[PDB]
Image (spheres, rainbow, N blue to C red):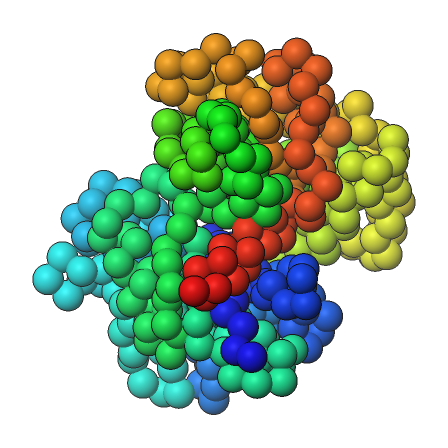
Amino acid sequence: KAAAIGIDLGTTYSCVGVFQHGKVEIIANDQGNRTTPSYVAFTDTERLIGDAAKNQVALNPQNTVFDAKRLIGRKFGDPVVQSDMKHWPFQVINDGDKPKVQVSYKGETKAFYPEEISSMVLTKMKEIAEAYLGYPVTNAVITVPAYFNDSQRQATKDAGVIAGLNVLRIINEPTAAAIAYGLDRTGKGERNVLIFDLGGGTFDVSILTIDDGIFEVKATAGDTHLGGEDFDNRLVNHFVEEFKRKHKKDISQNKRAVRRLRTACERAKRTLSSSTQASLEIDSLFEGIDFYTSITRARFEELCSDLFRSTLEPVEKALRDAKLDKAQIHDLVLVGGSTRIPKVQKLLQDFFNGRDLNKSINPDEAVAYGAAVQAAILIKS
């Protein structure tokens, strides 16, 4: 009676699931949250992981590590690492072409390999599972993007090992997503599946082929820095401009006012996925002025138009690299919280000639769900 877990070690957040009593439970942490930010903060007195780390990122930016997934398994010299560095507030150093994150922790300067940071997020996922199950957990399946190379998969494996996990297998995120939808168990036959993964920060399009239960990646396309946060920026910039046009004051130089507006915008954006309009109500936003306004879905769609239509560019590219016509795609799977946006679903559906989208599994949890299903299948031997 020792169940294995499935972990989606995400760029911005992580999610843990377990197949137990004939179904998957996506496990909530102590706060009741089913996702955990992939953030690790170092203070002068303690190390914080998850929401406590994200909460204070703007307070202690040099010592709050996120995006470790953008560094893991890569060499310091990699053009990807060298470009990502210019926009992170934390220091990235090297130990013979191996990148490391350098921080201040308890009055000491400490350096960590990306797998050491991710092992900290993984230890949190392990504890979360253990609190739920009521017994230790050591066996796990960890997901990775389909585009990761041997070095990136090995370093993810290393992060699991440091966390005291026995990594049963490293599997592709779109593969876990298709497994969550049971697309691997259709039976005798060849099927083409397209995974449309629009996250908080990343956009990934994967085309997989499933034949007699076996998976083959045909194409990986996407945008490494497009996501939910970009739609928030559009809403923020819009309301920074609206406040200025109404009250003739620029709020953008006040950190707290920008932060409070950004929080209200992100919630307004979520409300616009189920309603046609959202209210934005901030007391004493700037110079003591209350900001009470609204935004319609149509207005939000216009502000993000480029970002919305751009999601089809990697869909079109993926079909080309896969040497497939759009009619040859049997199944469409939505992953990532931003796929709840009606226009995102409309653009993709219209493109695939009204084809139904597999969206009944929470898009933030679908990857962990498939990994948990897979972990139970591997351990069943």
| Residue 260 coordinates in the image, percent (x, y) | 72, 55
Residue 272 shows in this picture: yes
- Residue at (47% x, 42% y) in the render: 175
- Residue at (73% x, 70% y) in the render: 32
- In the figure, 22 relative to 74: above or below? below
- Residue at (41% x, 46% y) in the render: 172
Q: 329 or 298: nearer the eye?
A: 329
| Residue 164 coordinates in the image, percent (x, y) | 38, 79
Residue 198 shows in this picture: no
- In the figure, 255 relative to 340: above or below? below
Q: 188 or 252: nearer the eye?
A: 188
Q: Is residue 183 left or right of residue 286?
A: left
- Residue at (69% x, 37% y) in the render: 359
Q: 318 or 21: nearer the eye?
A: 21
| Residue 256 coordinates in the image, percent (x, y) | 67, 59
| Residue 340 coordinates in the image, percent (x, y) | 71, 38
- In the figure, 111 relative to 85: above or below? below
Residue lying at the far left of the rendered structure: 96
Quadrant of the drawing holding the N terminus: bottom right
Give the image quarter of residue 241: top right
Q: 255 or 71: nearer the eye?
A: 71
